[PDB]
Image: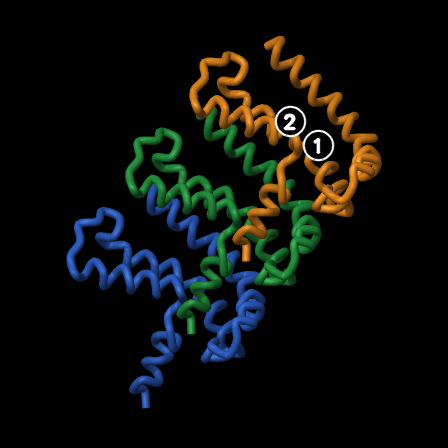
Chain colours: A orange, B green, C blue
């Protein structure tokens, strides 16, 4: 059944860590907020997360879904980070472009 | 008999996870709602779900119908997600287009 | 004798699952109803069901007429659904066209 399973697929079982910050700030402003920066950046952040999503999801596929086994998992987390930080490049570049425009 | 069997086919035994969110928000507004966003987006969401439906349904065919066997099913769920997230691309692009228009 | 046998043929022993919803809503409004959507959509729904009927009936011919043998029948039901959902495409497209006109 698609219930919570293909919806899990829809979420990639969890969105990329960018959308974690996105959703936290999203709730914080859904309270109320006049922030010019966080008026409508929700659309952009996921749109940027697109190209990253393939790599991050596949790199989490073979990686453990718990990630609470050990802090030593940071190395495998860092093995993923070898290009996840190359994506963080794009993330911060998107931050620069958002600030500029 | 078509009863709950070809109707199951009509629903694909469950609609794509997009329509899960669609129907939840649908009930929430059927209570009552003036939301400009959720006045009549029901038509669009299924229409978008069309092209995705073939892939998602066939990818759920050989996949288990329970999906409550293990959280480890996320990997096979993620094996489906390899292109299900490519469809999530289209989903969020549709969100962008809906917001723009 | 044609009695309940060629009448069974006339009904295809049961109409396609579209007409199940059609007849349920039909009774619900035969009670009474001012619904602009469900004033006279009975004609269209069967007319749309035409092209689907050949495939669905033949796909139910070799399939069991009980369909209460197992929930596992969903897979064979889903084997039928491989193109039954391709027909659900047409079904929802017809819904879109009905809403537009």
- Which of the labelled discs sits on residue A52, or is there none? 1
Instruction: Decide which of B98, A70 is in the foreground and name it.
Output: A70
Q: Quick check: do tags 2 and 1 share a chain? A: yes
Where, by quadrant of the figure, is residue A25 drawn?
Answer: top right
- Name the residue: 62% across, 8% down: A100
* Vertical arrangement, residue A97 with respect to residue C34, above or below: above
Instruction: Farthest residue to the front: give it.
Output: A70
Chain of the residue under the numbered disc 2 shown in the image: A
Mark 2 vs mark 1, CA separation in Å: 7 Å
- Name the residue: 17% across, 50% down: C34
Locate residue A33, reporting x and y percent: 45, 17
* Vertical arrangement, residue A50 with respect to residue C89, above or below: above
Contact (Cβ within 8 Å) of mark 2 with mark 1: yes
Label 2 crowding class (10 Å Cα cut-off): few <14, some 14-19, many 20+? some
Label 1 crowding class (10 Å Cα cut-off): few <14, some 14-19, many 20+? many
Quadrant holding the N terminus of chain C: bottom left
Which residue in the protein does label 2 denote?
A: A48
Locate residue A85, reporting x and y percent: 78, 26
């Amino acid at each position: 059944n698609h219930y919570a399973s293909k919806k899990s697929a829809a979420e990639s079982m969890l969105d990329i860590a960018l959308l974690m910050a996105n959703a936290s700030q999203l709730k914080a402003v859904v309270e109320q907020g006049p922030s010019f920066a966080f008026y409508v950046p929700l659309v952009v952040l996921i749109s940027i997360s697109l190209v990253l999503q393939i790599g991050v999801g596949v790199l989490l596929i073979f990686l453990v879904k718990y990630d609470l086994n050990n802090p030593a998992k940071h190395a495998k987390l860092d093995f993923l980070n070898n290009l996840a930080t190359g994506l963080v490049f794009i993330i911060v570049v998107v931050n620069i472009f958002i600030t500029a425009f």
